[PDB]
Length: 133
Length: 133
Image (tube, each protein chain N blue to C red):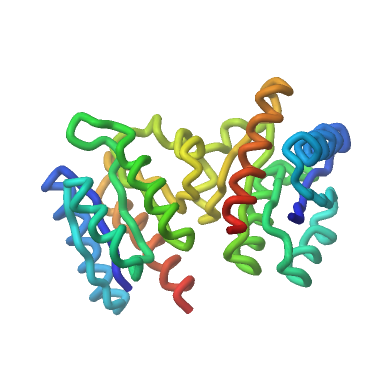
């Protein structure tokens, strides 16, 4: 399965990509991820290719909070079958996902511990595989 | 466009159904709907026909709260494409929807005035509209 990540902060990118690898070995699931903090580069991966199934978006991006929400709408448009998952530290945005009419599978707080963080990343990947028939 | 409503309180049934008629005449959209307050009766429609694109679910039902979530999971299972929006008076459940791995489009609070409540339902109607191309 292919995964796209919107993250402009490296340390969270590596925390996630590291975990995506662990699940790929433990659970034995072929996972290939792409991460960028460049909104334009990320969008090229949406419009120009409808192949990805899972998306990890950070909301607050380059001084523009809710930019992830906007980019999420773009995913839902160019790929209505896309599984959108939010990874952010702005916990107060949890109830704001519905306004942008995205249908997020999950909303993960970055602040939670690594064990449970890896757990909820696992759950979103498992959900993805099952939904891949 | 066919809409499935799950609501155990009669007053809220009419309130929603009025709006569905008003949206239907005002913005000129043919909308046909079925309503019930019984889970098994509601499953009949689901576990039978999935022409239903839109599902308006209450969550607190007959003393059993979080029941709407259970029905929604069934809806999500039988129909991945299914649009699921919650209409509950329980605000605290707005963040819980993710746990049940439903991809709820919206989460509508009942306690708001009828003016904006209609605007809320509109949004979900016009979304399903655009999704039906």
